[PDB]
Image 1 (cartoon, rainbow over the protein chains, first blue to last red):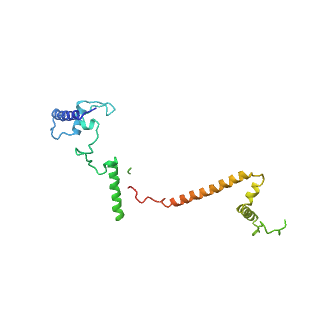
Image 2 (spheres, one colour):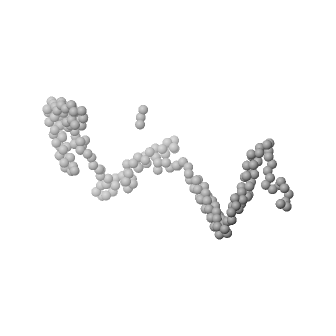
Image 3 (cartoon, each protein chain N blue to C red):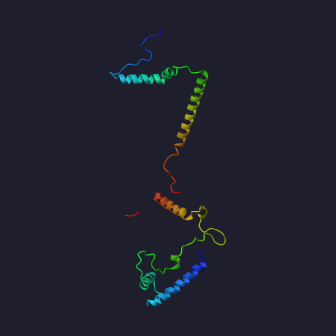
Length: 111
Length: 86
């Protein structure tokens, strides 16, 4: 399991490694981007493995490691969303919005 | 035997439609219960069995009428959803 401190240290390491890679490739570290990181890592570590995921990768720790839940209530205990106790706050919020849009109208190649 | 003939259970044919007249006669004999009487009289039905059969038929008719009334009463709600989404 990946504790948040581990992810924080990974983020710091990625930032320092990004500045190192920009130093190596002669580019300005400030404007150095993820496309630039991909190009530089493809040049420095050439790999013709057919699997694009078996090739060397230098990604942000957020992207490469999985994600976790979000906090749904603060220290006072009150949930942030008014539809929290449904257990499907996002879905029912979306349905509520759609129904309101339909009510407003009633008053008035792709998949 | 002692009654006048060709009045009871008699049907006239219209424009030579013999089959329609015969089927109307069958309808009349069935609706008046005569067909059921004739079929039931072939063998003797015991009084207890007769009583049980009549009780069962009466109760079945009552129950079916009540169920039909219930479904006809609750069919009013069967329409397009007026609060779709919510």
